Image: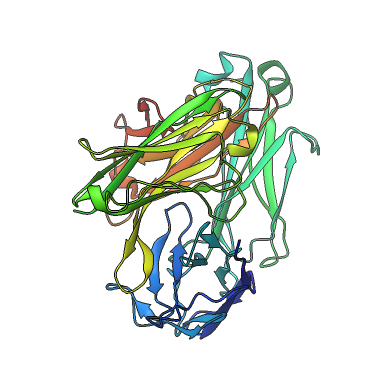
Length: 220
Length: 222
């Protein structure tokens, strides 16, 4: 096996910037014969298959923006993206297409830094359709914020909080570089129908005031 | 016209089998190398079998991870590349892709498939139960916000969620699945849209497509 070393493995740039990830191999990918390196670069956007970027160490595949360039030969290759843009958010693999087994390198995630945005919040009561079955799930959606670090607190009725809470972050938006998260408190219809003022309130670096969508009801 | 489509995937128990297939069209299959690549959940692309052009006898090659349990073959008349997977273990849970290993100057993978998810688990299938996410017209400030909670299902595999609505103003956010209490998942999917695009007594259908199975759908009232 021929190992491919990729670094850094995370890149955080502001876009409009110029970047260079590297990728060395433990063995030469260069023929002694045609003189061409058998190294490819693939871009993998969040939730899509990989797509050809550069082949040879340097040929840019038709349709790829001229922002992307790669150099090197033998063992140390690089990929420069000349003016980072919000779509560029992906993992970039380099691969040995020299011989078997073909190997890949760890990857290098490119994340975009942007100016702080603040969350829009929403509280959606548990559904009737669902009550009528045991559970009652209150979903809180926090949209379009940056940075991503955001704590969310669920004070059921009085002041409360717990391990009956699921939280999920979205990937970086490839349009604004903002995140989203949904936070879901799922208790029992009984349990549910005990208290009745249900709140959600995030504490984001943007504002100081804990941000808090709330709702009271449950008798109904 | 160079297209690759792979199918055959979902749950299988430790010790079971799957036959993954990759429908290849738009080119002369009979003489391009076809390759299988997997992607475990928080990990690099890892390469597994390889077929060869009816050019030097459809020879194969397997990675150590799989040499002995996986078997690669092709239905040359039909233009399908197969991956017989015997003796799965949890370790094999990944998105599996077929790729064309093109050769001109150099070798490279010019076309990849979309993937197919194989979860190797002892657990068992629970289809989601889609619940509507709407707000009492005492909560909508316009734009309206609607969603579907896709709830308590197994495996996670892959979930495509679509709305019976699109255009200019109308965003969809699909949140990744989260493991709850049970060893089962939940996801949500919200659709925000011009309030005059989701008035009343109307409704927009949210469609979930999970791994390998039939579409499942709900109509959520605005």
